[PDB]
Image: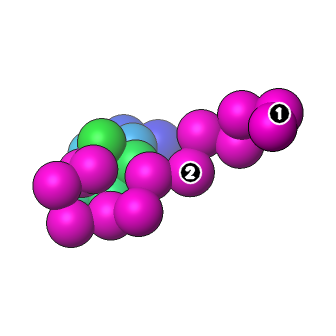
Amino acid sequence: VLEKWRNLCGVVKNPKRRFRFTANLS
């Protein structure tokens, strides 16, 4: 279980293109 964590970072750690949703309580 690593290819999933290395592929997720491409979106979870890509605020440059991603809207970035840390689910912070408004």
Find the residue positioned furthest to the top. Answer: 25
Is 16 or 12 nearer to us in this picture? Answer: 16
Q: Residue at x 24, y 51 (%)?
A: 14
Write down the residue under mark 2: 21
Q: Position of residue 12 (x, y in %)?
A: 40, 48
Looking at the image, is 1 positioned above or below residue 10? above
Disc tally is 2
Residue 19 figure quarter: bottom left
Question: CA–CA distance between discs 2 and 1?
Answer: 11 Å
Q: Amino acid at mark 2?
A: Phe
How many other residues sit within 10 Å of disc 1, few (<14), some (14-19) or many (≥20)?
few
Q: Residue at x 56, y 51 (%)?
A: 21
Looking at the image, is 16 positioned above or below residue 26? below
Is 3 or 25 nearer to us in this picture? Answer: 25
Q: Position of residue 17 (x, y in %)?
A: 21, 66
How many other residues sit within 10 Å of disc 2, few (<14), some (14-19) or many (≥20)?
few
Q: What main secondary structure does the magenta stretch of the protein show?
A: loop
Looking at the image, is 16 positioned above or below residue 18? above
Q: Residue at x 59, y 39 (%)?
A: 22
The answer, for residue 7, to whether it is visible in the render is no
Q: Is residue 8 left or right of residue 16?
A: right
Write down the residue under mark 1: 25
The stretch in magenta equals 14-26
The answer, for residue 5, to whether it is visible in the render is yes
Quadrant containing the C terminus in the rendered view: top right
Q: Position of residue 18 (x, y in %)?
A: 32, 64
Query: Is disc 2 in contact with disc 1, using a CB cutoff of under 8 Å?
Result: no
Helix, strand or loop at disc 2? loop
Q: Amino acid at mark 1?
A: Leu
Q: Residue at x 82, y 33 (%)?
A: 25
Helix, strand or loop at disc 1? loop
Q: Is residue 9 left or right of residue 1?
A: left
